[PDB]
Length: 506
Ligand SMILES: [Cl-]
Image (cartoon, rainbow, N blue to C red; front, side, top):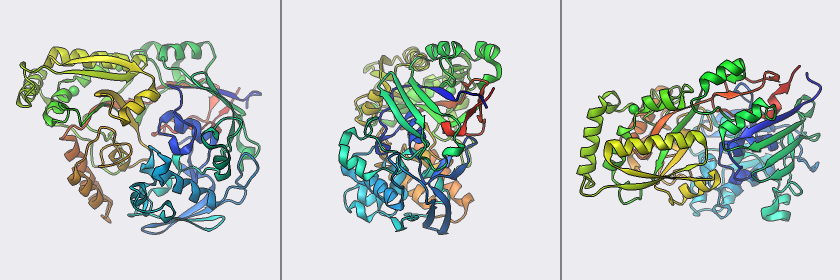
């Protein structure tokens, strides 16, 4: 081990919140999971390992038991118990809380009714049998339920701290948390600093003593800082840079694909975008082969639906008929769709295309705009905003076409269905197809995984034929991590890599 154990990690934007109930993003989960620990954790390899729960058991199809360790503590020295989880999950489910991430608790018994305000939060199917024993009842059987409990929004929250401090409870001077690190400094758009916690039950095995998170929007600037030794661990690499970066940094460039999809949000209540024919036309004209081979260049794979190849629970991704058509044929068909929809040359379309400030996103957006102009005569005006603002605008439908992207929360197709299920808190495009939903509910009754998969595949295909959004490609996991950073693996496919699992060598 190295004498010094400070780690500096770059994140793509200012974090939206450090309150587990309001955490929505990759950045929020990465930072929040250093500060809070749930029933389980995802380790450096991507494996689900014990968190506050030392063990768990699938006692019945709809029932899980979690046995908590007895020495889990909050940062103020108070014990962590079953009651803390009951409170946290009820709070998450309560619509008065206003969480945008109710999807994770939705599998729990009665959660839907509670979210809808039909039943009180106390009815939620999580119970403290005793201070160290948790019982969770689910609406339907979920074989992988423990994976979900490793995400930030299901971490416990300290009732007293929230009660005493209200909206200021996550401020460094007020916050109480139970993870391997405690928050020392939070300067928005500047830095977040955290220090190893001596109260964490597994402190003796936590090597990294200080973690610094720097929000840097521009990948090139991030690269410069990495090169200067200001950063040990980047978010990604600049678009089009793989070649020169590989030559200069070699194996520090950690390669792979992620279980994550890059796509354009479409406002489904838009007067034009509400027409499936318009959405489809916009989708079929974009050349994802050129996009990936010439613009992104980091191994990204063209995608036409939400399911990345390799995700458990479906048989295969969605690949539309036209994916293998000559472009000229693609364009003719798409122009005819616009005509059919009443948006021919007599009624030209203009949209605003909003993305979060970043060089890759800008490049992708410029490409889409030119593609749509030259092939369809559709005008997309580019607009860049801060990521936090973009997220809010998508929720509120204040953007028409928007840069979006989803990282799997767990390795099953269900995580991607959170984007298109009627009424889901993360269905921001506003799509609703009851047949798709009923097919999913049916799939989740199947006793056989094969049968389940078939139905989920059918439901996914059915949804994508409606083109509720525009999938572009599968995210590349490529990033730079210094040679002296140990513990990094290439098998963490959802890219949930906690600081406590790494260590500095040399
Ligand atoms: Cl394509």
